[PDB]
Image (cartoon, rainbow, N blue to C red; front, side, top):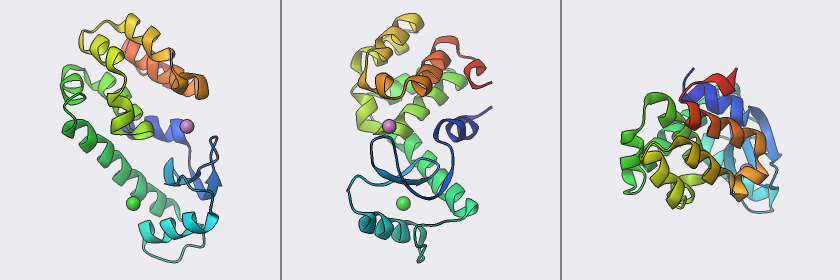
Length: 162
Ligand SMILES: [Cl-]
Ligand SMILES: [Co+2]
């Protein structure tokens, strides 16, 4: 398993614009378009990202290209952030993916903000980290997903994804 397979399972794939659980417009594999209430605006963002008049509808290839770009950006965000990079560097290949998963979902900034969990991961205090991560609005609003990611951190296996 790898990060792409993982996030595809976590985000799913929608080829039409949709309101997500928070009411934000989104498309493809977890690609946020806009946090704004206007479908118009989302439509506009979408055509700008794709480069054509989509009418809120895209192809699988188009979605996968967005995803690739999004995964790329999550990694760059990690390597760029002073707080995240040392942690990422200290982890193994499986746990690095759980970290990217979080950065993909919430942004470099959002993740850099989990100060205590970050420190625990760095120290390889897996169980503590897991407990700390679950005490969050993240977990409460995305329980099953969050549980998979935390489990992955905890065990350093892909078991939660089978
Ligand atoms: Cl884009
Ligand atoms: Co969410």
